[PDB]
Length: 7
Length: 138
Image (cartoon, rainbow over all chains, first blue to last red; front, side, top):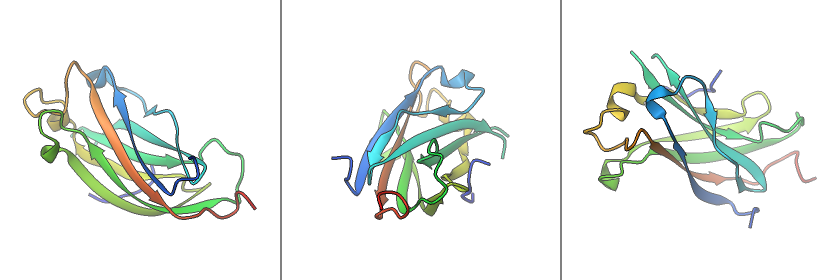
């Protein structure tokens, strides 16, 4: 639903 | 050339139903930097993790590049049914990739009747439009 780093 | 400000590239992941670790595509050069598709299984219920990575192998900590992109999982039966999401991000050494851990449901992408998987292969696509990087080619 929300973007982020793969971390 | 590699200095291009935008490009569209694809990466087909094989034995997809059996994916267990993150997989990286070969690099596509845009603004003379290496961009890659990163895919990995996640669990919000299992989901497809889909990220765009930039200049990750470089030991530099001075670079940065803002880019917008369209991450898309290709539907081979009908292009209009391809699943896409847009992103906008300032890529740098501490945040060198960006995307969605829960891009789409694993059950949906692996459903043989949906049109995203064939012979256990799924194709990922990225259309990236990047600004001129900073801290690279001084």
